[PDB]
Structures are given as structure tokens and as C-alpha cells.
Image (cartoon, coloured by chain):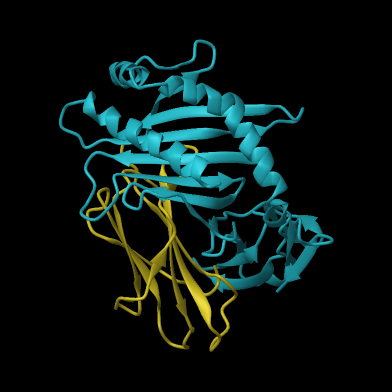
Amino acid sequence: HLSLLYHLTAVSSPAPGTPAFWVSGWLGPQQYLSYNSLRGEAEPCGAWYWEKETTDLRIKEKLFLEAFKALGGKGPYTLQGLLGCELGPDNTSVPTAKFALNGEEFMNFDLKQGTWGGDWPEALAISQRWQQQDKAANKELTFLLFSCPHRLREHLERGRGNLEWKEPPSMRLKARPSSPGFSVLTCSAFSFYPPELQLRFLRNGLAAGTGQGDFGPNSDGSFHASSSLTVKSGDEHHYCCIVQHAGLAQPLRVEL
Amino acid sequence: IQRTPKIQVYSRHPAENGKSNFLNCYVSGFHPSDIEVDLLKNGERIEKVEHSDLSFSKDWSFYLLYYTEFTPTEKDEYACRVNHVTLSQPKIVKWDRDM
């Protein structure tokens, strides 16, 4: 929330027709941008000039593929990057520049000396190649220190609409039997936004537990949640499910 | 490293027998990014399926959402089939109208 993040991935051995490099652009918990090596253009997403973006990402595309060049050795390799910033409490922007190799963090960008750093040999290899790219590190520094907070602030202005979005969840509470002598109570929340939701169980007014619950997205950007709790058969009606969400004027109680 | 995928199946809206809904298969926590996902009609396949862009969470693991428009019947058992390098045989998870 109040953060602009680009999720970058490049793979050395893409499957046929698949792109070697793709990026997702996120404004808080919402995706607004998408890009990939195949198309070569930055496209908008879910209800969200643009050139400054399709270019910035084209340069990034070159760098990620370039990283495979002097990593050498038979892959396959998966290079990931996290680039962005977030407005902090004091209206201060905090940048993010982390990199992963085959799922493991190994590189970062040091604002102090303005370069990518890390101890792994491969980080030393990639960092050195990137330093040799025309103005690459200057652009990195410039984006984390200036371009990012700026674009963030702009999207916040010209896009306050989708950020103030509020969708209360449709609740459902069902009881089903599991292991002998017990039933499992499942409390589900459907199609809500923002993503911050909270479920808790109560037992005849008493504070019960916060069951085992998953959480996930829906094709439209809204979310889904559910929480399960195991209770003794016949003790079901003694429970209530309480949900707290920004789209509700007050905590909603759900009975069987 | 390699991480075995986590699977969740649920509808967009609460299940209303006869009303147009949406079936979601949400795979996440896996690495590498190579994955194969399918939505099953009591054992069959849907040629009409869509998905979100492949993305990753803060721990670098990937996640993806597969969805199919639909209308719930009264006697079937929908499921999601996922194949990944970390699985001996494809994992099969069915949809429980409750979750």
C-alpha cells in the first residue's frame, strides 16, 4: 500500500513461444503494468507517457539477459529482481533493490557507492558486467533515489480512484464432519478489497481461536479468505465467526 | 533451490447452484517458474481457461492464478491438476463448495 514495485524475472532456457523476460508492475496490492520480451511493450492492467516505462524496462531486459552471458556454465538459471520504493511514515521514500538467483537472494544495490554488491562469485560476475553497461548504474541510482518516488507520487494523484476502492466481503460459515467425534467449522470471505481482512471465532461470547486459514486472489483483483477450526460434534452452534474489514462499518458476526 | 507448489481452489462468489460463477486455482510458493495447471470437470479438461501473469512474492517464490468462467451443477466434483518438477505425479485438488 503506497508502494510502487516491479517484479522482474528472466530465465535462461524458456520453453517454446515463452518469453525469456517478463515484468509485473504493482501499485500496492494492485497490478497496473505488465511487460514481456516477446511483445516488447509495457501494457496496462486491471483498470489502470507510458513510453518512459516501456524504455526503462527495455534497458532492464538487456541487463537481465546479459547476466546469463558471463554467468556461463550450463544453466538453467532464473534471475529475479525486486525494484521500487514506498512512501514511509515521514513521507520519506524507501527504495528496494534486491536480486535473486534460482530463488536465492544474492545481490543488492548499494546507494552508498552506487553499485550492485554481494559476496557470491556469480554476483561478482554479474555486477561487473552491469558496471560496463553504458550508464546502467547511474540509471539504477537515479531511479531508486528520484524517478521512483516521483512516479509513485504521480500514480497516486492520477489514480487515487482505484486505491480508495472498497469491497465488503460476502461471508459464509459452514459446519462439516471430519475425524470421528469432531466437525470442522469453515468461515469463508468472498470477493473483498482491500486485502487486509481478519477472521476470528467466538464460543458463546468467549474468544476462541484464529483457525487455520488460507488466502488468495480472484481474477478481478479482489480477494478470498477462509479459516477453519476443529470442534467437537454437537458443539457447532456455540460458535460465531467475526470478520473485520475496511469495507464494513463495523465487525460482522456470522452464525451457523 | 526448488519449492513444491501450494494449491488452493475456490469460487469468486459463494456457490449458488445455477448461477454463473468463477472457479479459481491459485498455485503459489513454487520454484522454478515452470508449471502446468489444468481445471478438471469431474476428470476432463477445459479448453476455455485463463491465467494471471506469473509473479512472485517477497520470498522469491512464484505464484499464479488460473480461472474459468462457469455455472455450478448439482452432482459434479471439480478439481485442479498441477504438474511441477517437484512432483512425482501431478497433484490433484478438488473444489469444496465450503472453502
Judge whether residue A134 can be spotted in this image: yes
Q: Residue A27, percent across and down?
A: 60, 46
Front in this rendered view, residue A161 or A59? A59
Horizontally, is B26 left or right of A156 in the view?
Answer: left
The C terminus of chain A is located in which quarter? bottom right
Front in this rendered view, residue A175 or A191? A191
Horizontally, is B20 left or right of A194 in the view?
Answer: left
Front in this rendered view, residue A103 or A44? A44
Q: Residue at x 54, y 39 (%)?
A: A5
Farthest residue, direction top: A113
Judge whether residue B28 can be spotted in this image: no
Farthest residue, direction left: A74
Q: Residue B6, percent across and down?
A: 41, 53
Q: Residue B50, percent across and down?
A: 40, 67
How many numbered dots are placed on residues in this image? 0
Query: From what the image shows, is residue B25 above or below residue A164?
Result: below
Horizontally, is B2 left or right of A157 in the view?
Answer: left
Q: What hue represents chain B?
A: yellow
Query: From what the image shows, is residue A206 above or below residue A170?
Result: above
The N terminus of chain A is located in which quarter? top right
Q: Residue A167, percent across and down?
A: 70, 64
Which chain wears cyan?
A: A
Query: From what the image shows, is residue A89 above or below residue A22?
Result: above
Q: Residue at x 69, y 54 (%)?
A: A198
Front in this rendered view, residue B28 or A106? A106
Q: Quadrant of residue B94?
A: bottom left
Query: From what the image shows, is residue A250 above or below residue B59?
Result: below
